[PDB]
Each structure stands twice: as C-alpha cells, then as structure tokens.
Image (cartoon, coloured by chain):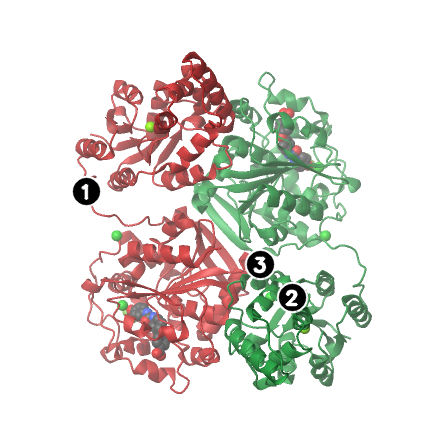
Chain colours: A green, B red
Amino acid sequence: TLRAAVFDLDGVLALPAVFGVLGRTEEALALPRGLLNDAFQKGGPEGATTRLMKGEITLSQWIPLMEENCRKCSETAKVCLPKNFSIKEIFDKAISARKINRPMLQAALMLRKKGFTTAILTNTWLDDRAERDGLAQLMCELKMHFDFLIESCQVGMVKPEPQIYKFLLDTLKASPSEVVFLDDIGANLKPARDLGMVTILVQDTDTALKELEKVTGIQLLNTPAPLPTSCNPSDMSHGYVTVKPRVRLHFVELGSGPAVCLCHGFPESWYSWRYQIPALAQAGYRVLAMDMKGYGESSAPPEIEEYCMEVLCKEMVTFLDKLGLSQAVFIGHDWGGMLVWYMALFYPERVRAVASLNTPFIPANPNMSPLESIKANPVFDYQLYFQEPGVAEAELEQNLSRTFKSLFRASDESVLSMHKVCEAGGLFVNSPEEPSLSRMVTEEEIQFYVQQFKKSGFRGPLNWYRNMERNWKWACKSLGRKILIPALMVTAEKDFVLVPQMSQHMEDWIPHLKRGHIEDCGHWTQMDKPTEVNQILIKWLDSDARN
Amino acid sequence: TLRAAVFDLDGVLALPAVFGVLGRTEEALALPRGLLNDAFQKGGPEGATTRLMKGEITLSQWIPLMEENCRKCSETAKVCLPKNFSIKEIFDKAISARKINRPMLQAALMLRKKGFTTAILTNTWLDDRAERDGLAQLMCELKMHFDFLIESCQVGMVKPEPQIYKFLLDTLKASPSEVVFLDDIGANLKPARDLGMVTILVQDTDTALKELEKVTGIQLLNTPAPLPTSCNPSDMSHGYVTVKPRVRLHFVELGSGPAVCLCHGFPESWYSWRYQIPALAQAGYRVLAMDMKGYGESSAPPEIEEYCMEVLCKEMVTFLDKLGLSQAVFIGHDWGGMLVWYMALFYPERVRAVASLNTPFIPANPNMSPLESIKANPVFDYQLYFQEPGVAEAELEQNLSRTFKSLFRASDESVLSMHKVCEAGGLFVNSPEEPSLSRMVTEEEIQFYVQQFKKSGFRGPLNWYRNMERNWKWACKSLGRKILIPALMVTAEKDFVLVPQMSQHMEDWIPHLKRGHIEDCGHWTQMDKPTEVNQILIKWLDSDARN
Ligand SMILES: O=C(Nc1ccc(OC(F)(F)F)cc1)N[C@H]1CC[C@H](Oc2ccc(C(=O)O)cc2)CC1
Ligand SMILES: O=C(Nc1ccc(OC(F)(F)F)cc1)N[C@H]1CC[C@H](Oc2ccc(C(=O)O)cc2)CC1
Ligand SMILES: [Cl-]
Ligand SMILES: [Cl-]
Ligand SMILES: [Cl-]
Ligand SMILES: [Cl-]
Ligand SMILES: [Cl-]
Ligand SMILES: [Cl-]
Ligand SMILES: [Mg+2]
Ligand SMILES: [Mg+2]
C-alpha cells in the first residue's frame, strides 16, 4: 500500500487546461485541425517547446519561435493565418483563464491530512511576461498545500522522460509502489508504470477522484466542506514593533495589498484568527494579526492604567506610525471589537474601515456610572469578579489547559455560567478538572494558547476589564460625534454575553453601518463558523475598502 | 537662552494655507469679501468651527453646519451663492493642494539635530472624509521629525486659549523663556508672549527663518542640502521568517505599496540602506530591507555550500512564499547585486523588477573556470585571500571597530589596496590600528555594525566568496536565457573594484536595460551618495514597477 500522491498541474490541479486552448483557438479561427499543436510540438525533445520546459529559454523567448513555427506549419498545409494572429494574446488569456480545480485540491488536502506525502509534478516554464504575476499568484496559492513542487524548467528534466520520475522518487524518499500519480496525458503515465507506480488518467475530475478513492481507501469524493486553511506558527512572518520604551507589539503578517489589522479578544492571541489570515491574504490583503498588549509575545506591563482604551489606542496609532502606514482596515472581536470602534471614533484619519465581530459600539451614558451599567446586566456579573487584582488571575493560571478547554466551547456544548460568578466564588467552581475537548479545537491548538499564557499570565489581559471608569470619562468626549467611515457589525446568534440585541441602536451613531449575522454561533466566532466569517468579511472588504 | 521650538502646521510647516482658500474662493467666484470667513468663524468659541477643532464633531459633521452658515451669512449681506457651491469640494482641493513647506521642515530638523526639543502645535480636526488618507499621509511624514505633535481636536483645547500653551509647556517640560513658537496668526502669539515665550509671525518663510536664525544663533537659512532621513533601529518594525529548519531571515519593514526587497552586500547589514528605507517608503513602497543569510539577526550556519547562489536564491523565494508575496522588486548592492540578477534569471515570475548598484550581470564563461577568471583580474586578488576558511575571518574579527572604519571609506580617503593582498599577508597589513572616522559614518553608526558582527562573525559573510565553482555550474544553465523584465544598472564612477566598464556588455543579455551613473562615488554607494541613489531608484520605480 501507498503513502504518497503526485498531481499534474495543467488539466489536473488547474482547469481549464492550456493544451485545450491549442484545440480551442483552431476551431474558433477555422484553422486546420492540429496546425497549432504541430507548431507547439515541432522538433520533439530537440524543438523549441522542450527547451522552454527544460528552462533553457524563457516564455517571452519562446513566443516568436512558436509564431515562426506557425508560419511554416501553415506553409506545408497550404493555408495562412489571420492578420492579427497573436500567440502572446492566445497564451495570455489561456493562462489567466486557468483557475484552481477545487475538488482536486481538496482531495490532495484530505490525503495529506490523513498522512500522505503530496507533490506537484508539472512541465512548466520560466514565465517572464508582463502579466506573469497572475500565474505566480496561482502557484503561491497551490504550492503551499504540498510537500514538494517539482517544476520542469527548474530541474532541467521534463515529462515523460524516465529521469524526472527518478528525481520524483528521490525527492519523495519513497519506493514506486508507495506512490500514486495523476496526469491528463497518457504518455506521462507509461514511465510511472514501468517503474511500478499506480497511475490515473485524468479526463473528468469525478472519475479520476473515484479511482484515487479506490486505490487509497479514503473518502475523497462527496466528503463535507472542509475548514479553511489554518496557519502553522513556525511558517509565519513574525513582526515586532516597539511603540514605547516598555512596550513592544508582536504581530503575524501575511499577504499583500491594503493593510488589514486583526485585533483579538479576551483571553486570546493572534492565533484566534488562524482561519481568517490565509483567506484574506488570498482575497488580496496584507493581514497584520496582532498580539494585543498583554498577550503572548507582546509586552504585558503590570499597571492597570496601561490597558485603558485611550492608551491602548494611542499605542496602535504608534504601531501604524512606525510601520509607515497612513491607514489600516481594523477588524476586532470581543475586546478588540470595542477597541476598534474607539479607533474609528478618535483616529478616523488612520482607519480605512472599521469592522467588529460580536462587540457592539456602545456609547458612554454620561449620567450613569459604568460600574452601575455593568451591575445592571446579570450576565456581566463575571466582570465584577475580575475587578479585584490577583483573584481572577489565580484561578485562570492554576491550570492553563483546563482554563482554555472550558472557555473555548461552542454554543451547544457549554460548561460555564456567567451569572452568579462572584456569589459562587469563581469561574470554574461547577466545571470539571479535565473538561472534554471542544469540536472547535484540536489538542495541539489548545496547547498553543497554553504556551502563550505561560509567558505573561492573565494579569495583563484581565486589566482590560479594570479601567471601566477611565474609559467612560474618555468616551464621553465623543458623544457629539458619529462614525461616518465604512463600518460593519457582525452579530453571533448564540453568543449569550454579547447578544445581537445589544447592537440594535448602533444606526443612530453609525448611519451607513452594514451588517452580518451568523446563525448557530457562540462567542468564539472565528473558530466556530470560520467559513461564514471569512465570507462575510471578504465581501465587505471588496466593496467597502478599495480605490 | 532657549532649547525648544514649536511650529504651527497650517501656513508654517505646510503650504499653501487652507485659510487662504477662504480668501481665494471668494475672489474666484466673485463673492463679497469676507463672506466665507464669517461663516467659518460664526459663533466664536461657541460656534461650529471651534467645536470641530476641539474634537466634539468630525469634519463630515461640520461640512453642512458650515454650508448652513454660508446661506444665512449671504442672506444678511443680501446676495446668494452659485448653483453648485460645494464646501466639501472647496475643502477637498484645499487640503490636498497643501504640501510640506520644505525649508521650514529642514530648519526644524537642523535645530533638533543641534539639541532642540521640537513640536507641532496645530488647530486641526478629526478628518473622516473619503479622501482623508491624503492628510493622514502628510501628517505621518511630518510628525516623525518632531518630539511631540499636539493636535487641538485630541487635547480638547484650541489656540489661542491660554490653557493649550500651559499644555504645551507641560509636554515640553520646559519654562516659557526656553521656547520659540512660530505661527501665521497674530492672535495665536499673544498668549505665548504673556507667558514669556519668544514669538515669530510667519508671513513669508525666509523672513520667519531669518528671525529664528537670529534668536537661536544657529545657521538655518542658506545651509547645505542635508542627507536624507536615516533610520533609528529601535524605531523600526523588525520581521523574522524561518525559511528552513536551521535558517531564519530577519528584515526591517517600512511603508506600504508594492513590495521592494533590499539586498545588502559584503560585509554589511540592513542598516546599509538606512538612507533609502524612509525615502522609498515615502515614495509609495513597502520596503523590506534584509539581513542577508550570514549577517546580523539572520541565521549564519557554518557550511560553505549554504552560501552558494542557488541555495541563497531558493531561500529568498521561500521568504516571499511565507510572507504571502507573489512578487517583489529586488534591488541589490555588491553581493546582493549579483544575487538579484540571478533571481531575475531563475525566478522571473517572482521578480516585479530587478535593480543593482555597482554589481554588473556577468554570465558564466562555459569554457574557462571561475578560479582562472578571478585570477585574471589583479584587483580581485583579495578574493583569493578569502578562499581559505578561517584565515580571513581571524583578521576581520580581531578588531571589529578597526575593520569597519578601514572598509567604509569614500573614494578620496582610502587606506586599502586590493591587489597583492595574498602576497602582503592580509587586508590591513599597511593600514593603521585606529583608522580615522570616514565622512560617510558617525562613530555610533560604526558601532552598530560592530554589534551585528559580534553575533555570528565573518565566516558566514565570507562563505559567499567560497562557492565560485558551484555558482559557475549553476549559472551555465542560464546561458540560453535573457532578462526581459524591467532592469536597472547603477554604476559608481570611483568604485575601483566593481568598475563601470564591467557593465558594458550587459545590453546583449538585457535588451531594455536602463541605466544610472554616479560621479564621485566609491563602493559604498548607499551612504556615499544617498540623495542621488534615492533619486535614481525612485524615478525607475515609478516608471518601471507599476500597474
Ligand atoms: O465579555 C467579554 N469577553 C468575555 C466574556 C466571557 C468570557 O468567558 C469568561 F468569563 F472568561 F469565562 C471571556 C471573554 N468582553 C467584553 C465585555 C464588555 C464589552 O464592552 C462593554 C459593553 C457594555 C458596557 C456597558 O453598557 O456598561 C460596557 C462595556 C466589550 C467586550
Ligand atoms: O567584491 C565584492 N565586494 C567587496 C570587495 C572588497 C571589499 O573590501 C575588502 F576586500 F573587504 F576589504 C568588500 C567587498 N563583491 C563581489 C565581487 C565578485 C562579483 O561577482 C563576480 C564578478 C566577476 C566574476 C568573474 O568574471 O569571474 C565573478 C563574480 C560580485 C561582487
Ligand atoms: Cl512548497
Ligand atoms: Cl478542529
Ligand atoms: Cl463565553
Ligand atoms: Cl511623533
Ligand atoms: Cl554622517
Ligand atoms: Cl573597497
Ligand atoms: Mg497536464
Ligand atoms: Mg496656522
């Protein structure tokens, strides 16, 4: 049995196939059947196309050698070509017309997720056209899901030559019977079979998947929608900005385009956005996923007043200042959510657009003190338990694994009351020592949070709840203002603390506020309904944060 | 005598002044003199404009309150306004029309450079228009050169109220006689004088500078062109990407826009680009200034083969891969220069444009070995001295301060032969123990390089010279190719090693190659002629690296 799987690019991981343009163009312009394909293949291994694929010449170099073959292919078949037959124009459109074959990719993902070493094996070229970035993009999205990407124009060998299959095996460190190989060209499979490999001719994807499903014994066709791409922390760009003598902010950076700044909640990290970071990068954005002050690799100074909203917000502006950014899109969840509204309200010149999950914009009531406003909500009782420094820390720090396993739970699997937490004498008092693992998290994912809170503990994070009076006096400066910058509010049906009802009055302060809502979704929106969050955020971003 | 200097924004650090649009618009549309200014000032401290400046309302909020004042200002003066009189359209154009008053900024820089604490004091607003980014940009470029930026709409006080001058002093931690204050409005100066401060009414800049020059006793007017902005290493965003189990690459990141990747030479760091990093950011780019493998905070593994071009180049591709970048503009100097040409030649899908200072693209000669090709140039003799592992390291590491002070020298102040270095028995054998400080570097700037090479030493850096045969066999793969991507070659007149002559044949391989040349310029181009380098690179970038 086999533990490797190798995929062809053109016509297998990517569709429609560029070879199909040779056929398509002919039919379209009423050219003799085969005429272009002859010109493409002219010379065999000694010909121009093979040289290109071996990386001796670039694409722009090959373009005229091909057009030159087409004029003499057409001479021998006694015809000529139209006045503006442009081979650059044919291959430009063909290559961008090519998209990822999603079912084939998901199938490669599933296999690897179940222990297979996966690789791409493609005959491709050194693309030096002006519009080459379109291809390089597709390759960056595709290659990241595979252990190896063997490109012909880099190894100096080409399918269907036996030597590149020897290379493939050396790279996979695997004997030929332990490997499947899918391709759309039969000639490319005969070398694989002679060495012993399992081979599949891809025509339609579904039958190709059916066969692969058979010989692997793994459900590939018709399986459920998988989660988005997570992030491997060791594979990320980690950034570090000193904003102040004693405060350094850490963040994870992925993608290019407009800066998008992701601000997590309590008690979380940048990893809370693992399912969003790759999506939005791919969507066309520069994701800057924070460790907010107090958490992880960001500084966590002891003082309570260091976590008031005004200080926190100034620091985020300095963060932009020092990164050379005039603006960013700001997207918050939980406490980050609140912060982000206050950024749009005090520093709108620096916010491209504002967006919050769960947390509504709540103005300060200038008559009534916050202490009483919080006291008026029985489900906010847990916040009063947090006020006394050291008490809440002791409990949360006692057993970091327990703490995270009992917090990170979906609406339909809870263990934790929020009312009567002071009275009961703690958060976990009626919840177990070893809580079950939630469906939202792997064991490994939990231990990441465990490591982060081994650094600076919970006093920093908790201090965010301990400036209620200070944030109130600040907030009251903004009571004459409105938010007229692009602004999205995303409610979660079954977040029993930040209830969607709390958001109902937001239109008074934010007139062109747009909305998103998620059915069956607890407090931990990002990992609970990642696909719906990714989708809602991308639509908004594309319509509300562009030139 | 005084050790502080405070500058007004509108009409002082930035011109033309927005108040001048009130006057300008009136004249332009044939409105009664003053009519707009009355509407602007309607109500005094109780009026709409003051509220705006105190930060009670945003700009978009104020816009209609102003238009509403204009309809009733025009009623009392028995006139009406044209059909499409738009106050948003007036203030949109006014604000972007505003540029930095460069002589005033240079004057503030000089003062601070000579020990003055400097600050901006401006009546300004919470800008929430769609085109607010234009302003936020100007403020980011301006604020970075001052110790404090006191904006009225943030402190809740406004000129000319005595309380904001009390704030100013508290912030400067300085008594009123130790501070100058420049402004274009006389009313704003009377509070400063009553407290005791020195005041200057700015009308024309040159006379305002003349006065400031007097009362400070520092040459401000007519002084020479200063260098560009350097970088304070503690103020930068520092990034860190693992590209491979044992190799982490460190880089400094500043700005937004297309990714521009700066690759330093031997034996240098990211700091070698200090004069370029802020310029290009401001020019509209995302500068990623590397520590190349072997140097500083980047990993420096012992093995010689880890610094061959092929490995180095693959690693840089992974660097892009993991940062989510499909391309970058690549700009190299010295060894970075060579690397960058080989990136354009092996991975053109990933290079937006290629650019080298000093280092020409030299193909491998397929007949003749590199050992002999290097041996054929008497000024390359120093490279042979480098081949034997440990020898060159011992000398360079013996006295790090000496080493850098004797390398980093301008064409007209040298101490170092390159011919006969093997024969003579070392680089420094006829150069002093305490070499003089070059005009290109401060003492502090030298000690930065000293600290970096205390980490991993010189063996890593030197290994870049120790794969001459391996790079040659690699290079010979590319002899059938050309570089048809945008490509700039910048020669340095008096670089006696990488002589401009070496670049003369580059057009054969690179047909649309563009050029730059710098008179009176040694090997260390970036710090020798920073302004000319910045200027040459920005022109090219704007024409050759955009959509
Ligand atoms: O509640 C949370 N997060 C949270 C709640 C529970 C939780 O689980 C556990 F408590 F830790 F066990 C973990 C995190 N965050 C805050 C609550 C306050 C809210 O902001 C408000 C809302 C209303 C008022 C008011 O009307 O007075 C004030 C602040 C921002 C988000
Ligand atoms: O020479 C330098 N840098 C340098 C030279 C001198 C120097 O001062 C000191 F030597 F360290 F004292 C410090 C750095 N870099 C290399 C030289 C080789 C060049 O690439 C070539 C050029 C020609 C050939 C060939 O024709 O064989 C090969 C490689 C890339 C830049
Ligand atoms: Cl890969
Ligand atoms: Cl999971
Ligand atoms: Cl909860
Ligand atoms: Cl500042
Ligand atoms: Cl200097
Ligand atoms: Cl030199
Ligand atoms: Mg194929
Ligand atoms: Mg002024």
Q: Decide: marks 3, 1 in contact (CB < 8 A)?
A: no
Quarter of the image where the N terminus of chain A is located: bottom right
Q: Nearer the viewer, residue B306 or A40?
A: A40
Q: Are marks 3 and 2 on the same chain?
A: yes
- Could you say whether the residue bearing mark 1 is in a helix, strand or loop? loop
Q: Is residue B237 left or right of residue B195?
A: right
Q: Nearer the viewer, mark 1 or mark 2?
A: 1
Q: Is mark 1 within 8 Å of ligand 7?
A: no
Nearest to N terminus: mark 3 or mark 2: 2
B475 lies above or below B100: below
> In whole angstroms, how far apart are the C-alphas of marks 3 and 1?
53 Å
A449 lies above or below A222: above
Q: Residue furthest bottom?
A: B367
Q: Nearer the viewer, mark 3 or mark 2?
A: 2
Count residues near mark 2 (Cα–Cα under 10 Å), then give few for <14, some for 14-19, many for 20+: some
**Chain label for disc 2:** A
Count residues near mark 1 (Cα–Cα under 10 Å), then give few for <14, some for 14-19, many for 20+: few
- Could you say whether the residue bearing mark 3 is in a helix, strand or loop? helix
Residue at the spot of label 1:
B222
> In whole angstroms, how far apart are the C-alphas of marks 1 and 2?
62 Å
- Identified by mark 1, the residue type is Asn
Q: Nearer the viewer, residue A120 or A178?
A: A120
Residue at the spot of label 3:
A235
Q: Nearer the viewer, residue A9 or A250?
A: A9
Q: Position of residue B522 (x, y in %)?
A: 25, 64
**Chain label for disc 1:** B
Residue at the spot of label 2:
A146
Q: Is residue B210 left or right of residue B43?
A: left
**Chain label for disc 3:** A
Q: Residue at x 30, y 39 (%)?
A: B105
> In whole angstroms, how far apart are the C-alphas of marks 3 and 2?
14 Å
